[PDB]
Image (spheres, rainbow, N blue to C red):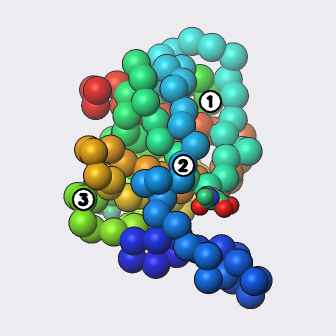
Amino acid sequence: YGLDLDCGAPGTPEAHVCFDPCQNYTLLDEPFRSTENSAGSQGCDKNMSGWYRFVGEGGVRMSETCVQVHRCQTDAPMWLNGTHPALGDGITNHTACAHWSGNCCFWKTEVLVKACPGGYHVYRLEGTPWCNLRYCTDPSHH
Ligand SMILES: *[C@@H]1O[C@H](CO)[C@@H](O)[C@H](O)[C@H]1NC(C)=O
Ligand SMILES: *[C@@H]1O[C@H](CO)[C@@H](O)[C@H](O)[C@H]1NC(C)=O
């Protein structure tokens, strides 16, 4: 990835093919991701790949603060150990932390975040480091 665009696999004939993540994401409207949701059969975001936008009642952004365990329809909820970028900051690299066993960063993994025209953010999410972990959404951001 570059300042504004993400590109194809290095070392392949698609390595020069780049796109704006703000125009090429998977849309998720999954209220169960809410940091306030304590129900549901725990699941795991192990299959995630590429860029994602979150919408709906569960919230439109990842949480910037540690989430209590057994929220977001998962066991170890994941939150953004960083500050969201502003539009014009480009693609930014961040740490996501999973809360477990008295440790708000028991697991960590890299996530990319970009602010987009129209007042939304997109996230590049590549699996999880363990299960059951999920990337939560904060419903305070409507
Ligand atoms: C969208 O991004 C994925 C990777 O997340 C890529 O494989 C695909 O080619 C992209 N599509 C377009 C139209 O840019
Ligand atoms: C990540 O979280 C820890 C614990 O709150 C904090 O010390 C650190 O400054 C955070 N890092 C960023 C980039 O926000």
| Tag of residue 75 | 1
With 34 as the anchor, is 85 left or right in this view?
left
- Between disc 1 and disc 3, the foreground one is 3
Expressed as whole percent of the image width and height from the top left, the position of residue 41 reads 69, 16
Instruction: Measure the C-alpha gap from mark 1 to mark 3.
Output: 33 Å
In the image, taking residue 141 as reference, residue 74 lies left or right, namely right
Instruction: Say whether residue 40 is left or right of residue 22.
Output: right
Looking at the picture, does residue 30 appear above or below residue 98?
A: above
- Ligand 2 contact, mark 3 (Cβ < 8 Å): no
Q: Amino acid at mark 1?
A: Asp
Q: Who's the residue at 34% across and 25% down the image?
A: 139
Q: Is residue 139 visible?
A: yes
Residue at the (73%, 45%) spot, across then down: 47
Residue 87 is marked as 3
Q: Which image quarter holds the C terminus?
A: top left
Residue nearest the viewer, comparing 40 with 66: 40
